[PDB]
Structures are given as structure tokens and as C-alpha cells.
Image: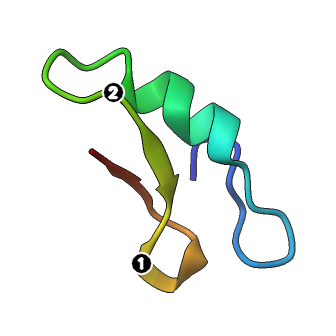
Amino acid sequence: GFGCNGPWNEDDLRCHNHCKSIKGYKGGYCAKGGFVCKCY
């Protein structure tokens, strides 16, 4: 989700923008299955 639609269309930036909008995290990337924007 969040820009990232999976391995065919991953989006480090959209995930990043989502995760950096959440206090505590700084980044986000397609982790689980290549779909889920995991926030770090």
C-alpha cells in the first residue's frame, strides 16, 4: 500500500512519506511480501 503496490511497483518514497508522517519513525519500505510499507 501507500504508493507501493508490490514487487511490480514498489515505492520507497511513498512508504517513506507515510512513515515519516508518524512520529517515531523516519523511513518506510516495501517489506512484507513487498507490499507492506514497514516503518523504521
Q: Is 31 above or below relative to 23? A: below
Q: Looking at the picture, how far across and down is residue 1, in whole percent?
A: 57, 53
- Which mark identifies residue 16? none
Q: Is 35 above or below relative to 16? A: below
Q: Looking at the picture, how far across and down is residue 40, in whole percent?
A: 27, 45
Residue at the extreme left: 24
**Mark 1 element type:** helix
Q: Mark 2 vs mark 1: which is more N-terminal? A: 2
* Residue 10 lies in quadrant: bottom right
Kindly identify the residue that appears in the image at 46 percent across and 27 percent down: 18
Label 2 to label 1: alpha-carbon separation: 18 Å
Kindly identify the residue that appears in the image at 42 percent across and 78 percent down: 32
State the residue position of label 2.
Answer: 26
Q: Is residue 23 left or right of residue 12?
A: left
Q: Looking at the picture, how far across and down is residue 22, in whole percent?
A: 25, 20
Instruction: Say which of 4 and 29 sits in front.
Output: 29
Q: Given this view, does label 2 or label 1 mark the residue nearer the observer?
A: 2
Q: Looking at the picture, how far across and down is residue 25, in whole percent?
A: 23, 29
State the residue position of label 1.
Answer: 32
